[PDB]
């Protein structure tokens, strides 16, 4: 009697109210083992905004997802209870207020023992999530991104942008930098002083160039080595992908990962102790016929299958 | 306590699960006095398909709607119980099966005494609705369209298309042709007498040219004259609008009605015995940044205000 | 037996090889009384190019046209022999060569006594057409445009652009300026007297502001007064329309004519001695879901109805 | 010697670095009498953001503008010194900081005696402009909008959004409500009395319905009556236009003003004591082939012609 | 005196009536050795329709194709007689009527000994084609697709959708399942009971994952091994390609084949006994600036070169 | 005191007048060591025009570029003086007049000893550039393209189109064919007589197929071998890339290079004696959300870093 998506043999995929994976909507985190949550918030965006619309369009395109993973044969909704937990509370005018409200929501989700699978929103959304999930013990992370997002300040003394969240997370003791690995980093930078913080912290950084030199299998091996057997969060910024696969994103950088490579890397994360995940920076105003929304919905499903297994083991 | 849309003061319009007008979702028609219903079905389409996606995108853009009509000051959710009844069952592969399923759904809606406000879907969807709502007593209708939709058959012995529903309705005694008025008709025609049926059964047809000659107010008076005080349905085909206002439709014809005009006309229908309405032929695959979906949602809100008064006897 | 478009009762409008109006294709002008011709040429364009693609997309969207005008009840294909004459030869690299080739083609068309209905292409295409059709006796013209297109030269000693064809035509005695009327002119101008030429040679210029003051009917009467009973050409530049109706054009100017207005105006030209017409400046690379291509095809059909009466003496 | 746009006779409109009207760029307000300024800021936006990109795209499309108004025959660059003053400093992350920075910039502009013609940015940008221009003596205003923008607070204790700037302005004594007129207001409203503030402080509000009843000329007379001979600012929110003319905006409402109407209205404001103007809410991420950016550039040119007369005492 | 495309040295590619490859139009199959046919029909579509417009836009974009293949140096129009045979008769309202009418057309094409090179339309179009071409002897097939299209029933007892054609073809004895190989299969499924029919039938299924493990050369070798020297049809569903290359399609699945990989695989089919081919599921309402139309037109040309050689040998 | 881009820590990237890389605008070539120049000219275009708009949209998207290359750590603006030199004079109506005017501009740039980094415009723009830069001594070239652009005549006796420039350049003695290597060539051709001129001239032609067989490293090695230590120009036609990465181009050919591969190949050109470069055939009317403009701006930056080093050594 787990929640199940609308039956596509009966209700065609273009029909029905568009919730994540066409699952039932829930308001109580305790009703679920994995909560699918939107965080429609782009207050942290320094360049092209629009990620506030990401969760709606990912919900929409997630109608194309089916019940069973074709490689792993994981059937997430049979394994555990999955539901659309709605959207976190957000304030488009007041960044500090949104940070507070978002964390408060995730504290409730966490207190119910529910694993969050979240759709942004820009990458600043991951900070208040980590504030909830990393409050008692620090998290490890596999982070897919064109950017490290460990900047310090923007336009004066503003410590909170989509480019600072993991620096903040490390400073706040929420993210363990030795169990952090970043994959796909590329594109022009401000100074040769960017990798300073990463080196100081011991973060493993696999730039696009090194990802290409290693190939998928060896990259994966290095990633799993870094995070080991500890509590691990997966954060997927769609701008890790080449703009050809993910045009709808605020800060594109050419020469990126393919959707195929992203699926292979995420699938190889199976078995880890995964305590949450997100798919961020889908930006519908820059998207093309919902391409990036569909990439987001699909990576969300790939991640759901793995979180279902973790939630199943801990139960 | 009446259903209410999400509070835009606490939940921004880009957020929240996108139901019609961000209202709560309902499975039981008995729960509501006005039922907001999707009919995602375009099996009747003879040219450009895509209206099957219409309800989803109209739902999406209906997030932009607020609580009070700024002219009439009608607050519909306060007046009656409104909600998102979901979508009528549909079958994209079997045309006759869809017809059966939709009618079955609308009979449940009708039996609970709920007035339907529906979003298509192509125009053929109005027939199974009429098979439920006109079953006991025939309907009058204010019909906004570039096309009469009173054709007989297509590509052979095919009697059900988006171009024939109101001929079938008249034949089936569901719709009274003497109480039917069609506004906006225009564009080239297949044969020299396309409207033989319409003239012979007494339908009042206000072509685009005549509506232009008459103007909004006169056009409005003629329409209210035709439907009188009887039970009346309003069917809004977005292709009545010029393609500049409604690009997202299967059968565009240039030289059409403005959105402003559509709003003045529908607003002028206040006070009638409105038993139901629909907005049909929104085709997202042909739409431009959701413009037509927003037109659809807005016309839906205009009609919802009228229907809310009707439901409140 | 007259050429006929594909039967939409047996072949849906999305199907069949896309000729103009889905008519048969012809190589021989002698075969036809009205020749539907593409001039895919934009060598005259000084800003945004792309009108070279216009004829292909207008052909595409002309599939939506049916057999009978719904107002005038003209059935053009029954009246006269109509077909798709293909495209005039063009050279995208050599401007003077294109001018030569197009004129040569149009002289063949003219010598067979066939009336041309042409789709551009930028406005410069009308000149080589006029070099054929106005060779023996000068033309009058009803010209719909945001721009007068009577400039002298561009970027130096360049006398042929989409902005100069009707000055050249007047200079070459192909076009009678006393029988020329231009409707819709608007938008900022290069220099304080852009229309020195026009006022001095006696062209009647109805700016957008005046057309607004006058209205359709008065504007129509003035236009028919100017051209009288003489042989008259109709040249429709889609940029006469507001960008909302015709986004797909090289030189847009806001605050323009509606599609409805364009149709009323052209329809009012019934009964004149029409010797030819064109629809120019459709630029698909700037178009939105084929909106402007459809405007182009539809205006083409409106003009085809008039030309069919003319060809039928 | 007055700044001049690039010569389109020698440099085509698709070429050259894209400054406003292809004018030279300036760092010093003292250099100019009319300053063309970008305010790329949308921190006030409660729904769809993207107006931060507005100035760049309006700059881009302003390349299509020429030197002389074709109706009034005003040649603005000849009358006064005009140029591209660049963009006001902005901070996309810190709302109050942006407010401070923009006001500081506009005080420099004001102190040099330069009249600002600004391109937003969402409507909240007008407040810091008013904090500079209405500092010494209060402004009157002709305000074109679908919305009154006189709300009190959003999502809690937040007093600065694109929906509150003119309430703040009135509260701060920067704007005289008895000399304020708002034209085009329409669309559903949050609560039954959205315009309590407006009626109580004496703002003249011309809803879309009334503007339709009155017509352009009467609407124009009423507006000039309200502002009189006092110092007057003109604020043009592109969402006043129907989405068909201005799709690229954050808060569209259907049934709006045509571009033609917007031009007639602004043109009718000639002769007033105009101390500044802006065009706001152009949102390129929602725009269609730059249509709204071109509307923005064109309305900017219309306003620049008026402001050039004002600056020339 | 074979038909030849409009001469581009004389008539620029944006001009002229847009027939397939700008060839002359034909009404009599007997006039041709290879017939280029549109099947503008998407009655079988269960999700996003629009493939009914595919043949028109593929005709349009096929204007960009030239006369000679740059690798193989095949010049198809010199080798054999090629022409635009127009569109098969279709009924957008009545699926069963379209099936009848389409097969009737292809029976005529087949009776004239003409090899069909067809543009859909959704994949259900391949069924009536096989009903004509496989009527005396069964066909082998190389099938490029994200989906097996061997489903049984949809929404009750409807046996005909774009997802059932090859199951129908096998049941009807038109397609020999031991000489069938499917390449590119990927994406979430309904149950782990999908590959049941394929295993029962002996179809060789090369999922996307296995295509990646093998690489192009070995995949090709396996494909040629399966079909051997027997009569073989090639059916190309553009959704085999990643949405980055083919956005205009009804049922996209991320992480697909590249256009480059598709060209290499098709070229390696040279020499086989190819008796027809199609390019299906181009859906213009979801296409972006005609990208997928051009991919369709180009694969059509790649396939034409190979069919020309087969038609040349059999003559 | 070199010119520097607008400081993004102070002026967000969506703001400020959009010059190349947001640098200051210059009118005097002598003020600069590397000049960034637009050539908004598509008179040579035989098919889909629109490249006349390329320089404007590349300027626009170049706002996303940062100050330092993340691999090479070249900081071009610190190394040498870089500026936006505006656009070359162009005449959209008169091809021969544009050729004259464009060359006259580049003669001035060259006379000041400034290295040009140019954005087209279609590929015919490279001819008048070579007329200026190759006037005293011939140039070598690394040329990335789907097409050789060594055709002879079009539509009669027109020797100047975007498809003839390098034939003209060789005939005029401006380009040394033995130090010319072309990479990415693919797509149907007119006759098997296309590679005639290339073979006669000794041009090294690395077709797409051979690029795939060699891989990036070996291709690069072959390219550097061809041009050796001599004066070398890099000309990058964005249609070398698959339409998935560069949709906005006049003459697309499917199955092309990835943006990632293009970056790797260009980076491997470091150390050569580079005397100019261009990025041509960006066509905004066929572009999708400025994707190709951004690819153009990024390749422009990749090339700038290398030209900065050459300009630094020669100073
Ligand atoms: Mn990130
Ligand atoms: Mn990122
Ligand atoms: Mn209808
Ligand atoms: Mn209709
Ligand atoms: Mn013109
Ligand atoms: Mn014009
Ligand atoms: Mn406003
Ligand atoms: Mn507004
Ligand atoms: Mn398939
Ligand atoms: Mn498939
Ligand atoms: Mn090239
Ligand atoms: Mn090329």
Image (cartoon, coloured by chain):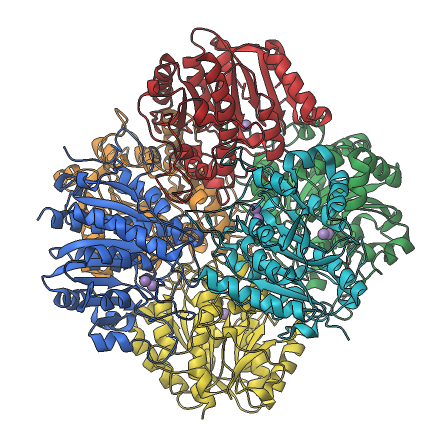
Chain colours: A red, B blue, C yellow, D orange, E cyan, F green
Is residue F33 in view from this perspective?
Answer: no
Q: Horizontal placement of C92 versus E308: left or right?
A: left
x, y (%) of residue D126? Answer: 33, 38
Instruction: Give the camera-side residue of F128 and B11.
Output: B11
Q: Residue furthest top?
A: A136
In the depicted view, which residue is nearer to us: D18 or A23? A23
Residue in view at x 62 percent, y 35 percent: A254
C295 is higher (above) or lower (below) than F288: below
**Whether residue B258 is visible:** yes
Q: Is residue B245 placed above or below F66 in the rendered structure?
A: below
| Left or right of D24, for residue F84 | right
- On the picture, is A63 further left or further right than C45? left
Question: Percent x, y for residue C1?
Answer: 51, 89
For the C terminus of chain C, the quadrant is bottom left
Question: Residue F129's spot in the image, x, y percent?
Answer: 76, 50
Q: Nearer the viewer, residue F58 or B140?
A: B140
Query: Which residue shows up at 81% across the image and 57% down it?
Result: E73
Is A152 placed left or right of A110 in the picture?
right
State whether residue D292 is above or below residue E4. Answer: above
Viewer-proximal residue, D110 or D48? D48
Q: On the image, which quarter does residue E314 sit in?
A: bottom right
The tally of labels here is: 0
Tell which residue pokes out farthest to the bottom in this image: C313
Q: Position of residue F174 (x, y in %)?
A: 85, 51
């Amino acid at each position: 009697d787990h929640p199940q998506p609308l039956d596509a043999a009966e209700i065609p995929r273009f029909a029905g109210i568009p919730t994540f994976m066409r699952l039932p909507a829930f308001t109580d985190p305790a009703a679920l083992q994995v909560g699918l949550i939107g965080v429609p918030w782009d207050g942290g965006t320094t360049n092209r905004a629009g990620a506030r619309h990401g969760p709606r369009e990912v919900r929409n395109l997630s109608s194309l997802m089916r019940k069973v993973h074709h490689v792993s044969r994981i059937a997430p909704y049979d394994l555990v209870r999955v539901g659309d937990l709605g959207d976190a509370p957000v304030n488009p005018i007041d960044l500090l207020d949104s940070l507070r409200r978002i964390e408060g929501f995730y504290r409730q989700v966490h207190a119910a023992g529910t694993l969050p699978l979240s759709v942004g929103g820009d990458h600043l959304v991951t900070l208040p999530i980590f504030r909830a999930l990393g409050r008692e013990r620090p998290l490890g992370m596999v982070h897919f991104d064109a950017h490290s997002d460990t900047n310090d300040r923007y336009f004066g003394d503003n410590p909170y942008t989509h480019g600072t969240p993991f620096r903040r997370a490390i400073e706040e003791g929420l993210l363990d930098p030795l169990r952090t690995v970043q994959i796909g980093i590329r594109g022009s930078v401000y100074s040769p002083d960017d990798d300073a913080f990463a080196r100081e912290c011991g973060i493993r950084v696999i730039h696009m160039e090194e990802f290409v030199e290693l190939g998928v299998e060896a990259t994966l091996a290095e990633a799993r080595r870094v995070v080991g057997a500890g509590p691990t969060y997966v954060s997927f910024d769609v701008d890790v992908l080449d703009p050809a696969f993910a045009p709808g994103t605020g800060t594109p950088e050419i020469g990126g990962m393919t959707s195929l490579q992203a699926q292979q890397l995420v699938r190889g994360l199976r078995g880890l102790d995964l305590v949450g995940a997100d798919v961020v920076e889908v930006s519908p105003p820059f998207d093309v016929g919902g391409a990036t929304a569909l990439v987001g919905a699909t990576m969300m499903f790939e991640l759901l299958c793995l979180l279902a297994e973790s939630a199943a083991r801990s139960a």
